[PDB]
Image: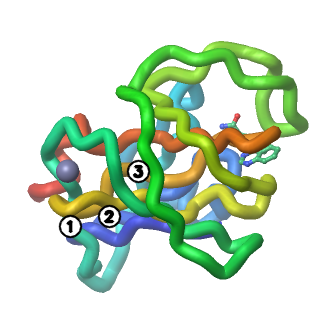
């Protein structure tokens, strides 16, 4: 589990969104595994606006933050899950790293701020849903 709290937005994996998230929905995109809901309190996270390919992510199944090199956001194949049919997830970045399903929501960050959240993984791969192109998270 995990979320990004930026301004009056809460960014979570769409597959982990709560009823309160759907009842206060701002935007959602199944192809990206992302959902954004509105919050009453202002958040402290800042979004990175960059093309970094190195950063650090949080892995809840190890209680550890790991430095990783990651690919550029792309259209990748993801295995069938009870959350998604096997399919093409967009804006996804891959790195070598431990992941379990519960780890989704962990933040990946670089020197500029939050880059994305754990979204996929398996066999020593971890995938991250990028949020750096969502410029509207910084306003309104
Ligand atoms: N965006 C998606 O397709 C959601 C899937 C749902 C099922 C779990 N998926 C995984 N995520 C992270 N780490 C993992 C480690 C081992 C196995 C699976 C995963 C993410
Ligand atoms: Zn950066």
Precedes in sequence: disc 2 or disc 3: 2
Residue 96: mark:
none
According to the picture, the residue beneath numbered tag 1 turns out to be 46
Residue at 34% across, 60% down: 109
Between 135 and 54, the residue placed more toward the observer is 54
Tell me the distance, in whole angstroms, between the alpha carbons under discs 3 and 1: 11 Å
According to the picture, the residue beneath numbered tag 2 turns out to be 9
Between 70 and 112, the residue placed more toward the observer is 70
- Is residue 69 found left or right of 31 in the rendered image? left
Against 137, residue 83 (above or below) is: above
According to the picture, the residue beneath numbered tag 3 turns out to be 116
Precedes in sequence: disc 3 or disc 1: 1
- Is residue 121 found left or right of 91 in the rendered image? right
Q: Position of residue 87 (x, y in %)?
A: 71, 15
Q: Quadrant of ligand 1?
A: top right
Residue at 40% across, 50% down: 116
């Amino acid at each position: 589990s995990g979320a990004i709290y930026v301004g009056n937005y809460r960014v979570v994996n769409r597959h982990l969104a709560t009823h309160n998230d759907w009842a206060n929905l701002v935007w959602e995109d199944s192809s990206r595994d992302l959902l954004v809901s509105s919050t009453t309190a202002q958040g402290c996270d800042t979004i990175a606006r960059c093309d970094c390919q190195t950063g650090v992510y949080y892995c809840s199944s190890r209680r550890k933050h790991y430095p990783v090199s990651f690919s550029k956001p792309s259209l990748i194949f993801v295995e069938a899950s009870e959350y998604y049919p096997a399919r093409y997830q967009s804006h996804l970045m891959l790195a070598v790293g431990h992941s379990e399903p519960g780890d989704c929501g962990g933040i990946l960050r670089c020197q500029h701020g939050v880059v994305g959240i754990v979204s996929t993984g398996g066999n020593g791969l971890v995938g991250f849903a990028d949020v750096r192109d969502l410029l509207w998270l910084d306003e309104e």
